[PDB]
Amino acid sequence: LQEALENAGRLIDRQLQEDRMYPDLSELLMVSAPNNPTVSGMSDMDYPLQGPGLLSVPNLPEISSIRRVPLPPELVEQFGHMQCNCMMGVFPPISRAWLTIDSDIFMWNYEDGGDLAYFDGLSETILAVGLVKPKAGIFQPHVRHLLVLATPVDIVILGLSYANLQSLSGGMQLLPDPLYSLPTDNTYLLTITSTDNGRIFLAGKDGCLYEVAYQAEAGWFSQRCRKINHSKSSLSFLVPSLLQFTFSEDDPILQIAIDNSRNILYTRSEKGVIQVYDLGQDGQGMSRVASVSQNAIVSAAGNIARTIDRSVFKPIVQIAVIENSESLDCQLLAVTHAGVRLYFSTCPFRPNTLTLVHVRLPPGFSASSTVEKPSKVHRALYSKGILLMAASENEDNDILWCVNHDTFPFQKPMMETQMTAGVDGHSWALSAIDELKVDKIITPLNKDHIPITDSPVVVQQHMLPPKKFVLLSAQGSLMFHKLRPVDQLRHLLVSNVGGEEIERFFKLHQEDQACATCLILACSTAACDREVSAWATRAFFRYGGYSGKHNGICIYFSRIMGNIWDVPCQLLESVLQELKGLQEFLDRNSQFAGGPLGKFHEAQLSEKISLQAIQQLVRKSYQALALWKLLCEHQFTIIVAELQKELQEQLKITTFKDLVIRDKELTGALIASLINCYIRDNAAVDGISLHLQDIC
């Protein structure tokens, strides 16, 4: 009654819906309850340590060091000629890193260790240089980013062009900005942020929020470059510092943070005070609506009904935004000097309130031994102190700590995928994935458009490359890359190459994600690594477990179609290759694969047909993608006035659902459009034949 392709599209849709039933971070943290156990401790965290430089990569890390770059001879020569100030940093929007010198800014790409791009026309020292989106309507379109430099005499703006040179990386060219210099104020400036539109908010050694505007004309009512104070919170109203101690008593703002999904700004001061800012509807105004000190954060923690002053004195040393895509209520992650990850909400009374709800503490595993130690588990609230919890436990060597959400433990919503990253240098900067690598778009690393399904890296394993991360040190850049379930699991497969092993996947994967990833390892890696994929084939058949094997097949197809189902040609080709290699996997596995060859009384038939529907959907998807190639072997604007414009739109709609499971009568119409247009030379007959293999 309903055809195999229709049915197959239903199963795929249902699989999509299931993968999209992923608990949201608010539910993942059940943030409704604010109690002490809302915060989540190390008792459920394991910290695998093997040692800096061990010749065995761990088999279950979420990050892996991939490369390092030796420092350039020239940067060091002039750098070592710096007289008064040096501030280094990373610009990951442009795959470039920075360092400051007493008088001048020179830019180089760490990926190539190419020539250094030199700018030395500043006559004053630059406290820090920000990498920001440009203001619309100012620049020639080639500008992808903007340079902001602050000097004790002026603050200067330099246009930037990142056109790729001899993608590996963007080749940078700098645009001269001859008039953009102005003092901010006697206030030092240390912290730079930018929104998606490109509004620039600035805080330095004073608890004030500057915004930098630039314009060609120097004025009587406005400086040639101008800044305005967005921190109107002092006002001096009761008795904090107006008539005693002088202006604001050392209001040492340390690091800012921006939430674009509500127009929200986060602050961390050196005293830990957090303020949340919304951008009014005017798009250039910002009004402070809350002022929350660190004392308030801690008061909240003690009010969590656990002790805080026993956890005090504790400073928060870093902040990480949590977008409303990431969490409905919870707005922010904060890091203490003890490595403590504090998760904060914010809310209006009419936000007008901010609540400390949940905290992830550093591991309970002591990374004392490099060498393997027996792991341990703690159901009880397990806690450790700054002396160990501080990632910078030693003064000479920073200790990288990397942790991602544990997508599989829907039974353990507070479980995380955990690793130990050993280095030897002092870390100076790390580009927050959520902070600057997701800058172009409003959404951060994400898997859906709502908090439910925002975190499951597992679903998007094939839709975007694994997130790579650049750690800034005083000697170079080390590249750590987020590891995927398929990657970790694959190396896990590697672990039984040289054992009772699949059961660990099962304990992780509930006999379905393991099946999905195992088919991925078999199918997707077959073109890259023959034996591991073969290991997956035998393993997938023997351990695929209606059974989890077919359902994992549903997982595979649905993830292949997650961007299309409800596209750049390279991604369409990758999808076609994925489907064709999958179809090849089963077709080349009739005897080996279960279900192609003719439980046993029926169920085996049940899987045979399941496979039949799957392969029919796969083959139709291949036909549809080839047909879309034909569509780019077709036309629409020349079609505007001879083929029934309403039908023309009918024709245009050739992507949504119908493309996978419904209606190639429209495809026959497309054939006629090709039949009449004939723009391509010696292509039609082939196009018609493609259709024949598509709809015959």
Image: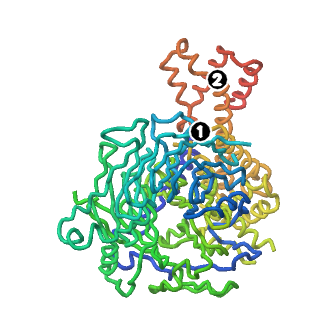
**Front residue of this view, candidates 334 and 149:** 149
**Which residue in the protein does label 2 denote?**
634
Amino acid under disc 2? His
Quick one: SS at disc 1?
Answer: loop
Residue furthest to the left in view is 238
Q: Is residue 507 visible?
A: no
Residue 422: name its quadrant: bottom right
Residue 476: name its quadrant: bottom right
Q: Residue at x 47, y 20 (%)?
A: 646
**Which residue in the protein does label 1 denote?**
567
**How packed is label 2: few (under 14 Cα within 10 Å), some, or many (20 or more)?**
many
**Front residue of this view, candidates 176 and 672:** 176
Q: Residue at x 70, y 42 (%)?
A: 165
Q: CA distance from mark 1 to mark 2?
A: 16 Å
Residue furthest to the top in view is 642
**Front residue of this view, candidates 390 and 428:** 428
Closer to the N terminus: mark 1 or mark 2?
A: 1
